[PDB]
Amino acid sequence: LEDPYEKIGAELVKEVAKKTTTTATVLAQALVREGLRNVAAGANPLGLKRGIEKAVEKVTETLLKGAKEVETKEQIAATAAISAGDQSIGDLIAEAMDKVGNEGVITVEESNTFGLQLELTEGMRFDKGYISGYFVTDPERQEAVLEDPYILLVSSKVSTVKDLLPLLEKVIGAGKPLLIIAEDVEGEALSTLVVNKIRGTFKSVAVKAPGFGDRRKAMLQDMAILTGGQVISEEVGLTLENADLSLLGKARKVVVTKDETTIVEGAGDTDAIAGRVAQIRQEIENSDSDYDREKLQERLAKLAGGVAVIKAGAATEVELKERKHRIEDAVRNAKAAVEEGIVAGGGVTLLQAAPTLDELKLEGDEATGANIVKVALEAPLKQIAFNSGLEPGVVAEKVRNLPAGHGLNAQTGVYEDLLAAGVADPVKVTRSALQNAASIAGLFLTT
Amino acid sequence: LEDPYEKIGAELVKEVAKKTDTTATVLAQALVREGLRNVAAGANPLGLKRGIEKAVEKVTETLLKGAKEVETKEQIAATAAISAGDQSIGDLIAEAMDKVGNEGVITVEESNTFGLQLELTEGMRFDKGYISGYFVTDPERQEAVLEDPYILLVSSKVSTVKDLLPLLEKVIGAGKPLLIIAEDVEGEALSTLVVNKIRGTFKSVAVKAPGFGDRRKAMLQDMAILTGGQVISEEVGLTLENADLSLLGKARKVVVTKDETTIVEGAGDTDAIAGRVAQIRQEIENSDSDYDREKLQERLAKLAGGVAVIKAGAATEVELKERKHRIEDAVRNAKAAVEEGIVAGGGVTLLQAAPTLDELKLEGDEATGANIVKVALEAPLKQIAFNSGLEPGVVAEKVRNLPAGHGLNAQTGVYEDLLAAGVADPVKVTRSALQNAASIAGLFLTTE
Ligand SMILES: [Mg+2]
């Protein structure tokens, strides 16, 4: 017996949570559900809202405090282990993470041998995707992939053709593909690119150069040095209309997604790349302004860290797929666990955070909004036990009474330390999930 | 044969000219002495003045009308190079106007490298200066300049001393200066900030946040993102007690004048910024009001625009100051050309304008007031002829006649096209000079 009016809300919250999950939705649905219930009893939608927010801030802290850290390769490997359901894969990720460090570029690649192989190379990644989604090549992943690409680096906009075709020709005359990173690519240069690309006459991609202004020119310089090319900036005697392939950097493979370009390989001497690396260590030392050291460490990281490449073997392209996926997922989990740490999954951490909300003194509407969150904190667990075909109220009461870290495991069915068991979660994820559920829920009780 | 009187008065005028704003001074003197003779011949002040005012208008629409427009990077470049006495400069500014766009912010600082530098960075200028002039650090330029500051955004009034202590404590702890932008900064809060600045204890500036109510609160948030800071509010974010330096935003430099605040190089995540600019473009499209719309789009033009910096090849001395104040003039002066156009430089475009006065209602005293104007229009060129040592009336008569758009030069001594010959003024400038003079003259007539 579910109230029609609540059901219609339920579905409006779900159809939203989609766009911005399973935890977050079930968690939102609960919040909104208790929301409408108290809004109907004459309660300020706003007061219930701010009250929720305070509750969520407080639970957040409590979750970040009571979070098991993940630092040793050994631990790290275990986290990735779970995320992929394979010890072999987690160890290879932990290896890679150790080599290039937790925050390093770790891509995964379709090897033709079989098994699982780790290789390191140079390259870097920046948060700038393709200009047009028409530059795409693997529709399912929504990525463009160039192979043995020439790299055009331009410190201005590109929109004419009169300066493009000189270069373009000389590049198709090599039967090589091309990545161009410029201030921007505007139509007549964007369309000549996207078009020749479908004609199949010319494969390529265009990406907005990262940053703004002068730092932007230094990051293009960076890329030239890490690619073996020279930045095209007519301001210093280097015409676009006049450029032999000599001015373009090369690499092994480029990969552009909706928001990040990855170059893999080089591309400039070990000398030059060392030179740049040092010079940047210099600026770092000779600066007393913290911003520039931030942005410098940043440039350094990409330039110095290089790229870890995980190689996977297979025979069905579908397996190659499922594999690439599984690994990629384990990476992002690994990285997230190394940042706020890790916590018992199963929705137990959340349901056992509820009693932290008594340390909170609020009055009326903001106090109810707090107690609403307190009830929602159990939704994820209760929801799981329901799919498990167990008794929601009943499981919420057999867990509300157990050691901090133990609850229902729907794999075995055996109430145990869920952390032990490898039912865990990166706490970033549990904290994100609550926060969104609480924005969504807030917005609802207000619009 | 100078008149001790007209002399004693031309002199008095020159001083009232050195007040705000020299073409105007010669104009104002010409209007006043001519205006005096006539007053000393019966003619009424109020009458002549009123007349001058109406006579100036006419000369205005006319000067606007005879305006060679400027759009292109060529033209624009050309203008600034004149007003700067360099063509590197001209270009460098025309360039600077290419990038940040035409009505964007273009800052000039004195650097220590040699080649005048164009750096683009994130940043912002808004229309509010220092709450108090005691924050001034360069007393010549009436400016407060702050290096590597920590910026504080507060959507409420700051008055209370105690409220800030826990934050100020932490900022003195870093040797960094602080720019505070609140609803206001008054009372013991204000004096405390000031006292400390005089002492040397602590380097700050306090500025009022722009606009009102909601719309102010939104711009604050804009400043927040552009800087990496978050707006301290008592409705979303937390109290001013137990605040962290991570809350503060930062930038390479803040310039606060009597009128304005520039934030150079905000320390914000370039993509955080981009994202917000997005949020605004959306708001614009969803906007139900053509008013709500123009506001949003200038907010947007501030974020996305950033700030052109120009560094002054130095090496090495007081020249770096002069050199700065010139580059600056060449900038407000190109921004000005574009906006209204250019005209016959020299003292010319003004002269040839007088023939536009006759189309008025030449009646009584106001008839004469206007007749005074047609006279002073000669003044500009007059003075110049007086320098290279010519015959005012002769040079003046000849030029008075030469086909619309030609006149004499200074280095050139050639009655040739002077626009082409490269000698010109922003209309606006020329229009302002006359308008000002008349306003001076305006006094000497009514008052003693
Ligand atoms: Mg300066």
Image (tube, coloured by chain):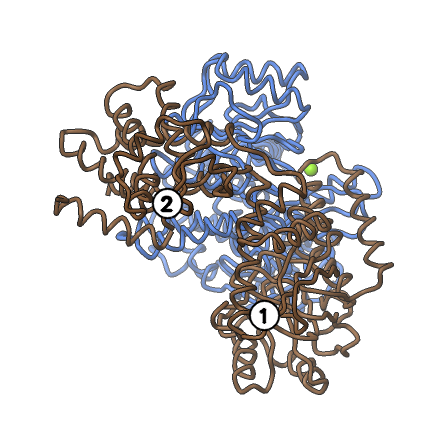
Chain colours: A brown, B blue
- On residue A23, the disc is 2
Dot 1 alpha-carbon crowd within 10 angstroms: few under 14, some 14 to 19, many 20 or more: many
Residue in view at x 58 percent, y 75 percent: A315
Quarter assignment of residue B388: bottom right
Residue A116 location, x and y as percent?
66, 63
Residue bearing mark 1: A206
Residue B349 location, x and y as percent?
55, 60
Residue in view at x 27 percent, y 34 percent: A394
Which one is in front, A47 or B295? A47
Q: CA distance from mark 1 to mark 2?
A: 37 Å
Of label 1 and label 2, which has the lower sequence position?
Answer: 2
Question: Circle 2 — which element?
Answer: helix
Quarter assignment of residue A118: bottom right
Q: In this image, A319 relative to A279: left or right?
A: left
Give the residue furthest to the right: A271
Residue B211 location, x and y as percent?
39, 36
Question: Circle 1 — which element?
Answer: strand
Dot 2 alpha-carbon crowd within 10 angstroms: few under 14, some 14 to 19, many 20 or more: many
Q: In this image, A77 relative to B363: left or right?
A: right
Residue in view at x 60 percent, y 41 percent: A338
Quarter assignment of residue A72: top right
Disc 2: which chain?
A: A
Q: Quadrant of ligand 1?
A: top right
Q: Amino acid at mark 2?
A: Thr
- On residue A28, the disc is none
Front of the two marks 1 and 2 = 2
Res B129 visible: yes
Which one is in front, B208 or B233? B233
Q: Amino acid at mark 1?
A: Ala
